[PDB]
Image 1 (cartoon, chains in turn red, orange):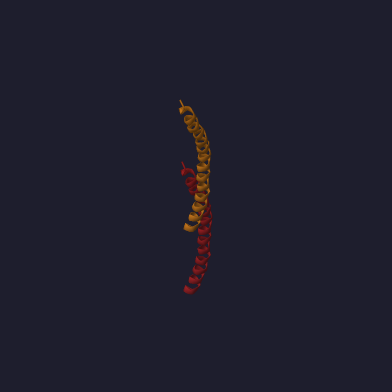
Image 2: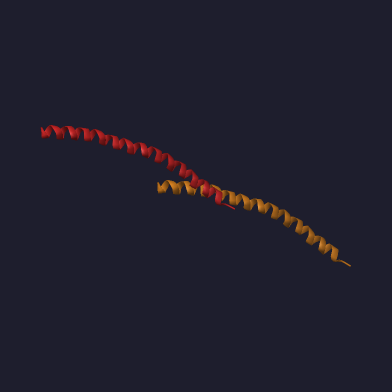
Length: 51
Length: 51
């Protein structure tokens, strides 16, 4: 009985962990978009600096 | 990420620098015209000097 419980818990635990990776990837997409927007802002600031 | 930022900044920086050269050339055209006007004035002064 103990082994069955562990096996169930491990698989389910494994099944939830994939979800954590998915959440990280989702955050990364948004973060990547933010970074892209930021790169443009820095370039614009450099252009803006000239007298 | 750092390299991308530098590359963006360098290109944009390079793009603004050409503009500096353009401004120098524009000033030089005006300056050249002023110099041409001045050359005539000096010659006129020399002509004017005679008794």
